[PDB]
Image (tube, coloured by chain):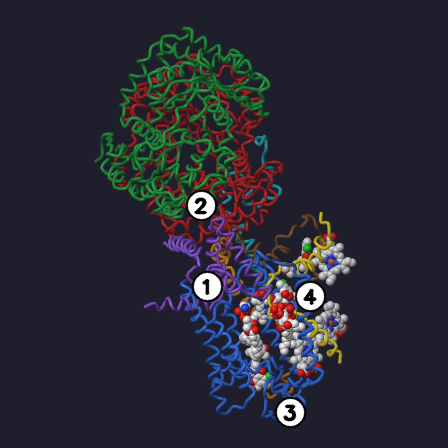
Chain colours: A blue, B yellow, C brown, D purple, E cyan, F orange, G red, H green
Amino acid sequence: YKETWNTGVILLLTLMATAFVGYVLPWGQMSFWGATVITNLFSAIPYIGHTLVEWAWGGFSVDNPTLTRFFALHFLLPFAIAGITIIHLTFLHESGSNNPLGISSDSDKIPFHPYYSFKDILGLTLMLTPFLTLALFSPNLLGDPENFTPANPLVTPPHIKPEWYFLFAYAILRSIPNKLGGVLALAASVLILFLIPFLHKSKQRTMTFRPLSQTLFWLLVANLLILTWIGSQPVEHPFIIIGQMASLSYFTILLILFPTIGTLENKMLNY
Amino acid sequence: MAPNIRKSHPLLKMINNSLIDLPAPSNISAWWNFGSLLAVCLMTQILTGLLLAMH
Amino acid sequence: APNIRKSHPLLKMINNSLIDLPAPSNISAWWNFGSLLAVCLMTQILTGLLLAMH
Amino acid sequence: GRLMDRIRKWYYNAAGFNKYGLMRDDTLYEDDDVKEALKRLPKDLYNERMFRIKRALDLSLKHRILPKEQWVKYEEDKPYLEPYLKEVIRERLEREAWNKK
Amino acid sequence: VHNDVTVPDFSAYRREDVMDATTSSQTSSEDRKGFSYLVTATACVATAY
Amino acid sequence: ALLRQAYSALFRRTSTFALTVVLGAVLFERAFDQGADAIFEHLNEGKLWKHIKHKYEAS
Amino acid sequence: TYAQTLQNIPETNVTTLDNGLRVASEESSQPTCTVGVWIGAGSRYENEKNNGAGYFVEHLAFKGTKKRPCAAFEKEVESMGAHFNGYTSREQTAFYIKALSKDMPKVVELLADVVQNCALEESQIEKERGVILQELKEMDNDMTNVTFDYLHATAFQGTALARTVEGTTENIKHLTRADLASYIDTHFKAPRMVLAAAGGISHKELVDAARQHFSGVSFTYKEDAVPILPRCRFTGSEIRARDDALPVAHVALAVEGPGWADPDNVVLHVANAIIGRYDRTFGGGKHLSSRLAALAVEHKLCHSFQTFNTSYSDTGLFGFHFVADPLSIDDMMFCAQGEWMRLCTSTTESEVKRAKNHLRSAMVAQLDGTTPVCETIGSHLLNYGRRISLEEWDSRISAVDARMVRDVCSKYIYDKCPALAAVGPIEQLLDYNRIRSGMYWI
Amino acid sequence: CPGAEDLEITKLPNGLIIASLENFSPASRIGVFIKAGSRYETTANLGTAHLLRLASPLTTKGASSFRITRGIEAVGGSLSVYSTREKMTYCVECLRDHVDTVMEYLLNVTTAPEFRPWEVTDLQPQLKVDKAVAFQSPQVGVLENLHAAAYKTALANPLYCPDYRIGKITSEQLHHFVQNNFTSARMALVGIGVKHSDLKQVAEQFLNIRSGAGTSSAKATYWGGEIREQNGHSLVHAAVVTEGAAVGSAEANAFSVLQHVLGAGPLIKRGSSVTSKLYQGVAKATTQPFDASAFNVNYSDSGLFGFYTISQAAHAGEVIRAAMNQLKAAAQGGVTEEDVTKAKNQLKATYLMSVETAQGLLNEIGSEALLSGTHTAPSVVAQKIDSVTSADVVNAAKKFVSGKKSMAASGDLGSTPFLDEL
Ligand code: HEM
Ligand code: HEM
Ligand code: HEM
Ligand code: HEM
Ligand SMILES: CC(/C=C/[C@@]1(C)[C@H](C)CCC(=O)[C@@H]1C)=C\Cc1c(O)c(Cl)c(C)c(C=O)c1O
Ligand SMILES: CC(/C=C/[C@@]1(C)[C@H](C)CCC(=O)[C@@H]1C)=C\Cc1c(O)c(Cl)c(C)c(C=O)c1O
Ligand SMILES: CC(/C=C/[C@@]1(C)[C@H](C)CCC(=O)[C@@H]1C)=C\Cc1c(O)c(Cl)c(C)c(C=O)c1O
């Protein structure tokens, strides 16, 4: 569902940018060093690079202007999210939802309400339970503590990690031991989502009836699950090696394997 | 004309035409519940967000 | 199909609400405030952000 | 050497679309050619393919499958669409090539 | 009938160069357009600035 | 005839029309700028620091 | 083989009688044949007060002469199995007869007796008055026509070409014996006529019969002078005749054409072949080579459409006409202009190759009978000056290619202000400004 | 360089006729004439002939729906199918250098059709259209009903598929109609602008399908009916006829001459047609506009003959009756030895001219080369024309006034007469 999908990817990137700048507002140690590293990423872009950083900061080193234009930015984006979400859902509606077996469900549709409205109310009370169990009983479980220490422009904490949801990328960035390569790998680590629709070779839509793709699919999940662990560990052996691996692994399972096993599977069905 | 005021009204025809009379496959699994949860989060984030922005 | 101005879920909107829109041939200048009002909004919003950043 | 056979038959039971009573062809994702092919299906073959599918969806909503007995068998799977589809794709390649000339 | 129908006189509005019913309006076209398109080209340059 | 020479070479082709607007906006700017600044500075002789300037400079 | 069969066709012989009349023919072993006199005089030649004379005349040229009244004329023709019929356009009238190759000479005399001694009995004139006034009530319900007239009517507005061939209602209601007379006198003159014939006839024996009955004399230089007409001005405009009570809508769009003389007319016709024409009963359907016909089929854009390259002495009309339902006029018009722009910008060699072969065949079907071959000869001398052979036409048609088509269509179509004529429930089609903008950027 | 050839005409062992004729025109026109048609239809497969006519552009065993159109279009060629209640004529027409190209499709269309269920059923809605455009001419509305009243079978079958049968025709009915009618013994592969050695080599080396009569048409019984169609339309069209003569029969020429004697459509634009008995006769009876003519149809095992009148709704009575007396008066010696000499020329003329157009010519060679595998010279046909005596004419005129009559009429018939009043 290409457009529904592409707007999705756009959503993801936007949510990421948002959550990032939010995390900078309390102006703690991560807040600062995060702000420093991420805006510094443009520095990898030749020429217009070192300048692009100047705006970003509003000065010649992170400071107050950065913090106010970040609060502005944070305040704004969520709405742009809500906006695009509307489009996401609109493109969707042209086609309709997909379903597990991946075969037309025109022979059997049902009114969203009360079937899925009730099902979603329930799905809500379920996510809500651990979300609240977490937020109420163990508040800081999921969050880095460096942000309890007011930013220090002179000291970068030794155990500087990003919020859990960015680790996997942080992991890849720390793989490529070259400024631009790491940056490109990082960009691609998310932007690669735009290519998925084009790397589809199976003659069937889902993996429900594709046991090989399934294994590959779950092998990929465990693959990310690892990068996250790696992202939470220091840049020392055996980690460094395990790291480069999982990354190399990530990009291969997506650009080479999947589309390959896919073709293979087609032949095994005699197509 | 339109009998019910659910299918004619320029607005309710929308709440109704995109979440109430919407055609949904009868077999979507729990993996399809994330759409709404994502949606709900957005509203919850935005709300709690403003409350904070006010301090 | 045929034109990508009337089918596209988006352009069908830019086109269906400001380009193929049926307008009375005799509206006077007192009808130009709708757009000016609109334009303000975008101008206000833009200059506003710029300021919120300081 | 019945290897390819041995494998295919394996993959066939591996997929498991037969547990729902679907023929290998009921699972094809409906792109442009497949859609055309289906319009060329004889009334009855189309109405049967429909039930098979409407039945598999109902199974899926219920989270069940057919009792082992009713499962399609690797050798009894009728490739009811395969030949239509191949013609659709052959008629298409002709056009495509003829417009470049 | 459609035979009794004719196109009124637009002399009150015609451009000087296509006022004469016996001269190829085609010669003065290149200009009539070049001028109107020059006004636009300028508006674009003025706004571009 | 410029109007015809222009139309035929510049305004006809919607691609060359653009090149004209750009190429033109460039020239128009550089000139409209000097002119206006020239008009303004003239209208305020000896009041601008550009004028006073030499009194505390170097030579 | 094609190439040769083209050069074998017997050349057309031409010889002029010292009174200006021109005689010409193509001899075949055909036992039957056709002969007629093609007069270069129509409605463009009429003024505002005599609009519809060339037509009021075409009606009486068969109701008898001075030498032989009605029944004697008709009877003398019918009884020998000949076919007398003709027509009259904006700038070219003609009267021709189809008969056995034996009556070749007896025919010539008949033709000459109509163009010179038309009776014009005033008993007949108050009858053909009610008859024409009737034919206008019929012709008026012919959309295709009501439309092309309105097209000229505004395309050449303010000039001579902007007039219908049938003329006004007031003219037909008041035209006098005098005017018809004076019209024949001023226009039906030797230097402006052409006796053409083809079939199994002796060019010689034809020219003789001519010298004998086609005998008018010329003293001054005036009589041997062929007037030059005051040029017609093309106006980019539109005329919208609306009636939402008509079943379908008719639309015609055109730009000014070059005129018979210009060689480009060849290219323009090749161009028109690429777009071609279509209509509800074409078996080809969705597979037709004409991109527009396809779309037409695919989306149900129309009931029919056709390109056209109408030429005149000094001017012309190059465009297209389609018929459609009220609710699809827009898309059709859209796709249509679209295909024109493709012409000016991205025509391929494949499209032209076919375009050429399609023209070549239409060019031969032009000469499928003695009447058609005679019509070609009649209108070739009268318009192109001499006779243009198929072998020649074909050489010109082969010379054309992509680059040529693009350069020429760009010449007469790109960024031009067209003339529009819409008739019927045309609400969906709209604004000249828009249609105008459809004239550039493919 | 090129001159004069000979109209050759072979006939292979299977009964397939091959009639060529090199006339060196820059264009050729090949055509397959067949003895098929709406008369071999039954109440069971009605309209299957009509649809077969539109199904000409459908995929065949050798060429595709797409490639047949694009293939013919590529060489400025053309395909067309004309048919009568008993004769189908598939034929192409291209420039000399492309005869081979346009042939393949002509061969593929007539001999190897597939009539694929889908193509076929996507095409059946066209019968709805094709029949609506044609039926715009009331002229074709009264002819349908005529043949219906004039017969009980075969020729009584409509030329355009009746409505109730639109969308109920099958690929089988198409196939079975082609297998049992397009048999080499009923087929003739004519051609113009072509050398016989080629047109022949193709017909043989390429053509096939079954041979031998196959199914045969059930001889047309005569009925003598009366179908009136009240429909408002201000102009009342009418046609009163009686069994005429068959094709090739002797008594034909006589009617053909009794045709031109009563008047067969004007020869002078906006004319008055004096040489037309019937016309003049009607004029001397009615005051307002009209037209009336000599109707003559020649079919294999039968024929039709009589007149046709177009008149205002009110003057329909006087016009039709006056049209009769004028036919009786000609049955009772009212024919000059001269009217017969003039009618003899008009007939030699009409024939001689109709063969100038490539279409009309190929259709002359064909028709004959299919109904006898021969070819009369335009010199022999000339004799048969004038070998008609002033008697034969007066006889045909009688055979009309005496035989049983059929009639068709459509319009505001309120003033039109019933057959049992003439
Ligand atoms: C603001 C973020 C997002 C929100 C709130 C959102 C919301 C929705 C909703 C409500 C649905 C419908 C219900 C469902 O099927 O889940 C949906 C469907 C979908 N979304 Fe999103 N979405 C988001 C992000 C994304 C992302 C990141 C992607 C792409 C990587 C994506 C891909 C899709 C697709 C493909 C569908 C169709 C699902 C199907 O096949 O049934 N969405 N989304
Ligand atoms: C896209 C939805 C949103 C996301 C993903 C989001 C995320 C975040 C994050 C990750 C933080 C840092 C939290 C922490 O660890 O302290 C944060 C803080 C904050 N956000 Fe948001 N936010 C969202 C919407 C909003 C909006 C729209 C507002 C207000 C209208 C808002 C205002 C703030 C403020 C004031 C803070 C800083 C103080 C604090 O951390 O409590 N947020 N946000
Ligand atoms: C954010 C404020 C507003 C904006 C940007 C806005 C914009 C527009 C626009 C663009 C139009 C169409 C063009 C026109 O007719 O002017 C319109 C029409 C209209 N607006 Fe507003 N509007 C605003 C406020 C209002 C207010 C305060 C009223 C009522 C007290 C109003 C009453 C109307 C009405 C009645 C129409 C129809 C105009 C007609 O009859 O043609 N608008 N508006
Ligand atoms: C509805 C459109 C808007 C209106 C009517 C508007 C109006 C105003 C007014 C009256 C003031 C006081 C101006 C003064 O100094 O006299 C102001 C100031 C300001 N507005 Fe807005 N505003 C609009 C949109 C925005 C938005 C959306 C932002 C930023 C995203 C913004 C940011 C500010 C800020 C930071 C100031 C205070 C500092 C200053 O006065 O320069 N405004 N606005
Ligand atoms: C995960 C990531 C960047 C993610 C972005 C930049 C995407 C590549 C594009 C869209 C976004 O806006 C994200 C914030 C960078 C790695 C990364 C971090 O996130 C953070 Cl918080 C820190 C403190 C460091 C320190 O070294 C880091 O290397
Ligand atoms: C955002 C949402 C539902 C939201 C609430 C807010 C309802 C409007 C009322 C009751 C609730 O609380 C739901 C969570 C549904 C999103 C949503 C969709 O847009 C679409 Cl097209 C589909 C096919 C589904 C299928 O499950 C879906 O969940
Ligand atoms: C806001 C706007 C137009 C805005 C711009 C921004 C265009 C999108 C492109 C070019 C411009 O610069 C316009 C000012 C038009 C508002 C607007 C409307 O919404 C509607 Cl329903 C109507 C009937 C009119 C009639 O005049 C109108 O002006």
Q: Amino acid at mark 3?
A: Asn
Q: Amino acid at mark 1?
A: Lys
User: Which residue position holds label 1?
Assistant: A203
In the displayed structure, A267 sits above or below H340; it is below
Measure how far apart labels 4 and 3 are at the Cα level: 50 Å
SS for callout 2? helix
Question: On the rendered structure, is G103 left or right of A137?
Answer: left
Measure how far apart labels 2 and 1 are at the Cα level: 27 Å
Labelled disc at residue A152? 3
User: Which residue position holds label 2?
Assistant: H117
**Residue G167: horizontal and vertical position, in percent?**
54, 28
Measure how far apart labels 2 and 4 are at the Cα level: 47 Å
User: Which residue position holds label 4?
Assistant: A118
Asked whether the residues under marks 1 and 3 belong to the same chain, the reply is yes
Measure how far apart labels 1 and 3 are at the Cα level: 56 Å
Tag 4 near tag 3, CB within 8 Å:
no
Asked whether the residues under marks 2 and 4 belong to the same chain, the reply is no
